[PDB]
Image (cartoon, coloured by chain):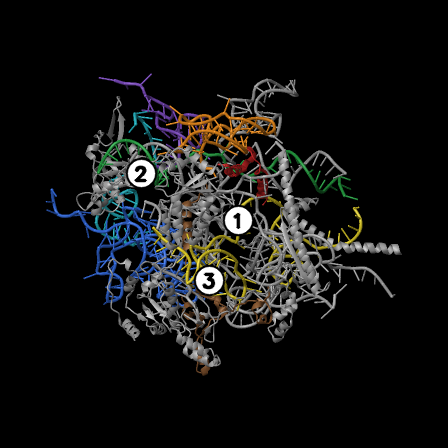
Chain colours: D red, E brown, K yellow, M orange, N blue, O cyan, P purple, Q green
Amino acid sequence: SRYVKVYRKVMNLQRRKTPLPWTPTFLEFSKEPSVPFPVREKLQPAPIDLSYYLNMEVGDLVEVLHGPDCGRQGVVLSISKKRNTVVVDGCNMKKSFWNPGVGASLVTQEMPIHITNVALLDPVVKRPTRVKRRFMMNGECVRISKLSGSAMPEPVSTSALRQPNLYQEYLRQKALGPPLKASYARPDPLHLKILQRLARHISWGQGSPLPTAENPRVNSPEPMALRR
Amino acid sequence: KRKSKRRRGRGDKSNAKGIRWKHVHQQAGRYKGPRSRTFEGGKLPLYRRIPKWPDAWLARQRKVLEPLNLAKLRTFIESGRLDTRFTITQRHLNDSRCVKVKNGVSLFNVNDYPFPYKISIEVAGADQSSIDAIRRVGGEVIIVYRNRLNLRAHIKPYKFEVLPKTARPNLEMVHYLEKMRA
Amino acid sequence: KAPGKYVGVKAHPLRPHDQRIKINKRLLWQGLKIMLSAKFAQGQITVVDHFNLQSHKTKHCVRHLRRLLGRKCPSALLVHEGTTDVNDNFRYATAHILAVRRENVEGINVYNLLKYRQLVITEKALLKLIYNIQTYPEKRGWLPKYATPDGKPAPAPEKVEGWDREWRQMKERERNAKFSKALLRERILKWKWSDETKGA
Amino acid sequence: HTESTRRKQQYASIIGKQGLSKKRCGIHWPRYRRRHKARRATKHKA
Amino acid sequence: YKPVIDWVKNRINARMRQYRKRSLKKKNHSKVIQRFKLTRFGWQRLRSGRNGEKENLTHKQLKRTMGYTFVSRDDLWKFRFQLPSHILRLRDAPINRNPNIRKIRRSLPSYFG
Amino acid sequence: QRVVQKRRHQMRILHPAQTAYVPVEQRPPPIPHSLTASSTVKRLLNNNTVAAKEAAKRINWGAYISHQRGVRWHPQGAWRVQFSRRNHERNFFVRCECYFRVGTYGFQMAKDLAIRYRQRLEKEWEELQEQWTKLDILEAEQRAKYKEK
Amino acid sequence: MQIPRDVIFEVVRGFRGRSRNCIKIARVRAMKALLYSSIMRRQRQRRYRVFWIGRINAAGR
RNA sequence: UGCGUACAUUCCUUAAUAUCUGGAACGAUAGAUUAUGAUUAGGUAGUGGAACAAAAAAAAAAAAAAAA
RNA sequence: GGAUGAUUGUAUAUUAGCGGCUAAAUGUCAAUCAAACAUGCGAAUUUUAGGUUUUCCAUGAAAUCUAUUUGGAAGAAGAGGCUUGAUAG
RNA sequence: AGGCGCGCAA
RNA sequence: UUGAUAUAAUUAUCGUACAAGCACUCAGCUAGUUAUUGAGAGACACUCACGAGCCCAAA
RNA sequence: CAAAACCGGUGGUUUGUUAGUAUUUAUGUCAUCAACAUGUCAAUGAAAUAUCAAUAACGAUGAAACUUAUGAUUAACAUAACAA
RNA sequence: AACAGGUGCCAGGCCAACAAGAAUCCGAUCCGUGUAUUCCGUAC
RNA sequence: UGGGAGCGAAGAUAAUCUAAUAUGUAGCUCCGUUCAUGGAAAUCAAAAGAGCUUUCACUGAUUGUAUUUAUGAAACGUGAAAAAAAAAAAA
RNA sequence: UAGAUUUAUAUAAACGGCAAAAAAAAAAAAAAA
RNA sequence: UGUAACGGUACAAGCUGUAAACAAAGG
RNA sequence: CAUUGUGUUAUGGUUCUAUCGCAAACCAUUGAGAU
């Protein structure tokens, strides 16, 4: 069929983050105005943060309900309220990349799971449950699970949960660029300092001759001077 | 002064193209006749009257060399676009834009006119008149066999990390090379 | 719902489309040169040492602009290179002067030059612009090349003596012109029109 | 047609007068305001 | 009830149509192309009767029949639409009515101006 | 493919005629183009024949040449005198369309009178320009005197 | 239109009934009125001339 | 031996765009308009030239006489 | 006209359109049934035929020929070519 | 990258 | 008033026809749209740029 | 031949001043289904926290009123007043 | 000139908790965010 | 979902009509869209070479199929985008 | 996140043969989705 | 999730659930 | 050149638009946090 190509083009226009940045160059003008914008329906349900109403916090034990990790149990490490997504320990191991540090050639790590695909676990029955916040007379808050009526254990602490995020380090290094030459990366502090002194003279010398063994005198820079 | 728009059907006195003949004396429908490019009536189309000509449509399919006139070559030499102290090659012609090489340059002379300069030139082909005119003043015409990849590497070696080794010709190209040598 | 039967239904409706057109880059280059010439002729060009400021206050920059251009200037385009011709103090000061617009040398257009009445250009940016304008034809390939390692023309060789003597003699013979039909028949026998569209 | 002719005549009658008000301009108020803004545009930075 | 418009679909379809329309190409007639050859002096064609009965033709007529000829000027408008990618730019003789280029100018002491 | 059709004749590609440059120290003035509007001259030029070519040599084309700007020949059978000027500041627009007819005066006498007419018009124009400059200076003097008060 | 709308409504002043204010009928009536004027303005010269002729004939007789 | 009768580029005002009306002329800081220059100017289909269509946008709505 | 009978009447059901039912009339299937109606970015077409909206000006046809079943479709023919101003005052 | 054109004279 | 004078309009048609079709009247809606694609081919098709050269796609 | 980020919080820009708007039932059908009813939530007014006084007249408020303010707006079309 | 909202209508300096004019003159009948002139704030 | 899978028409072009086009389209059922499709050669090519897969432009409306109508993002190739192969014998 | 929060929307599928009644003894019993 | 039926609330195109618009001052 | 008509004006008839809204993208800042 002779329409698949144009259909794919117009559909990619729906995902394009137009306008994209464009570097000016002499006698060249951007095509961004000619690129059309994506079309969307603006009358939709308002944003919500489902974690607030579900009483789900980092450090809670949850079970993945659907997908290739069905039945797997892990501790929540991160919650995105805007995306209503959750990172679960050892689940959705989808993001693999060249190792930015020491160890094996490749490293893989979790990816967010939508909060609706996950459920809190009852401490006694260990099945999907619903957690409600109750308040005592003094104002102490207690999270109670529907299935057994048990109080939720305190979330695992950030100190225990912490792990480095190697994908962000990989992204940082990639943004920096390809690896440097070993010779270029070798430090040369003495010659660098010589060049830095020369650069100081070049930038702030106002075109005075460089010092020599014959005349090492110090040339006084001129001030801007007021108009009179 | 630009051109005024000539929208139709906006009054009787407008100088736009008329509508009355179109309405009354023209066939109705999208195509105003049969949907075709060949129809001329009940009679056969001219092309179907005429017999088929396989040579005509095989000539188009034949792969052809880029022609270069010795007059153009002379003008470039005189203006200095090519250096006659060294062998002038297809790459030199391409880079001076005397001729852009796709399959190879072929020299042709006009009216058996003489050539004034002694030159050594490598090309893919050349007419007998061009060869005689070049050699009459001490010149030299060279033909180096090159496959498509070899010609690409000869014109644009800078696109190759490892240059390829020239390949041997087939029977047709051996015939052509020996004919050129003759 | 059909044309002539419902309000909002059209036979030839307006359609979304791209309004951009095409123009020859050579025409754009020539237009830039003409715009610079026009600004010089009409006295709407000023050359500045640099746009480096020691204060970020808008009022000081406004006073400098008023001193240079007067109190009746409609608008100005401030052209600089970006690195050592201007500084962040200037970028801060000009950020709220709605009558002036900052541009780099890469973004100079006939449109900008026409839109903004005055053109205030640093010497560095002016030289950068002149270089770009003068070297554009070479970059776009509008000038001849010489197929030499240096890229400059090579010496023109001399002609081999007697290279056209036979042709001259043949012309001298034919110039009698009394055997016209005989020569015509000889040419008809010798030569053949080609049926190809390219070449001889 | 008649409506367009009438609207054009009224616009020609009002658009050329400075200092009008919203109640005087009616349906032509945004057009009149834009026209006066354009006329002022030349006074900026004198 | 109101007739609400599906702008997403309408605009997507409009963009698709626009892109296709502005990327359309030329088209030639694969059958018409096979009977003709374009040369520097005009379109050429074979002669009907080449493949027919010819026992009653003389030698002159047979030579002409097996030769070739040019497409008549009356049939060129067909090519404009059947073979768009192959254009023959017609070149008639120049028509210049300036009296100074005429042979009678040699009998005048000057030109007309 | 944009193939330019070519014409061949006698084993050569036919081209439009084209002549070389013949330097001339002083090219003489042309015979007026107004003569080509006459029926006799039009037929002479349109008939490429021996009789036309002999009548061309018998015709005295030099008598129609005017050595005066603004005076020349008209198919009327008269000498046309023209003089056009536009002065917006003084609101003065002049267009002379004078005719000196051969039937009325004579070929040569009409020519002479037309030439004299054009010369007088030029002289009057010069004098008027001088007077306008003088009057303008006087007007400036009056305006300055008024502003003195 | 053959005649401008304003001219039509100005010419149909003083006419009878709908011809004064309805464009469809006013157009036809104004067309006829101006056509009659065009023809009769060309014709009236000889109608005046015959009147002069008759007056002169009576005076001479 | 007469006369009636239809026709005015006689007067006055406009127009001419598929290369031949003077004009390849006279002007020229952007054409003022030809006074005994010519042809002339009914028109369906078709074709062509010009003038409007009161709006919007644009970074050009004060160097303008006299009066204020 | 029938009115102890192939009678009349009644709740809820069955047969569905490239079809059903039909003591057979192309009768009837929600009153246009020789093949129901609703919906369909299946976004039906038309050698006939209805309309097609400012003005001024320049130029200006034909109802003919070939061939095809075609007052249709194809080609040709059909204009702008040229001229129309003069003194032995 | 590619496209068109590239004298038939001298 | 009186004298003279004049067979609404539109379309098709050989045919300037209310025994031909539409229209009470009026308001608004209501029909030659567009070559990032084609072109000047003896029934008409302009205009700038560079010039033996000219253009510069995706990015 | 010149020049050389991740998860929360807070605002702004663009989409979009250049584009459009979509949530409730009156009415049809056996049903599938079809289909922009009724101006606006709103007397008028910027303000009613300006509608007071009052059988009537003169008064009050208001820029404008017992009213071209105690709903506005063509033509066709409806009625009057004045005029030779 | 998009130096956003509101204030009787077009307000950078009247309100809007962090800058800056109750600025002056001229306005048929009330008002003016209007015309003209001018001062001030602005890394907004 | 003019993306992918299954089944699968006619009105329209061919001036009737058949093929072909429409079109592998509409309706119907099922996937649910870059965390996807697909995929690291028993590949393509020439006697030189390229190097999984994917996207864009050119080659080109070319070579093709249809042989009255039309269809055809062909293959190799060229210029770009993106770049990846495979943590992994247990602990 | 102080509490409370009726009824309908035919749901053992947070689950696994298909197949009426969200899942019905074997067989009869039949499938392009 | 979304929607609706009834009920309460100015007998309603709003809000709301028999606690039907409000607890924030508890061993 | 009517009191059965016309001219001029007036009063009716008449289309109804008052933002109850504004990222899922990008820019700039700022906490926690990693290096």
In the rendered structure, the answer to whether residue B22 lies left or right of residue B118 reads: right
Tags 1 and 3 on a common chain: no
Kindly identify which numbered label has been placed on residue B35. Answer: 3
Q: Mark 3 touching mark 2, by CB under 8 A?
A: no
Q: Which residue is mark 2?
A: A204
Q: Chain of mark 2?
A: A
Task: Report the side of O4 relative to C171 (left or right).
Answer: left
Query: Can you say which quadrant of the picture contains the C terminus of chain B?
Result: bottom left
Q: Position of residue P22 (x, y in %)?
A: 36, 23
The span from disc 1 to disc 2 (Cα, nearest Å) is 79 Å
Q: Nearer the viewer, residue A193 or B58?
A: A193
**Which residue is labeled 1 in the image?**
C4
Name the residue rendered at 48%, 49% in the picture.
Answer: C13
Where is residue A127, by image quadrant? top left
Evaluate if marks 1 and 2 touch, with contact meaning CB atoms under 8 Å apart.
Answer: no
Above-or-below relation of A129 to E33 = above
Write down the chain letter for disc 1.
C
Q: Look at label 1 and name its amino acid.
A: Gly
Packing grade of label 1 (10 A; few <14, some 14-19, many >=20) is: few
Mark 3 residue type:
Arg
Residue projecting furthest to the right = G61
SS of the residue at dot 1? loop
Q: Are marks 1 and 2 on the same chain?
A: no
Where is residue D46? Give x, y as percent. 50, 36
Label 3: how many residues lie within 10 Å, few (<14), some (14-19) or many (20+)?
A: few
Labels 1 and 3 touching (C-beta < 8 A): no
Kind of element beneath mark 2: helix
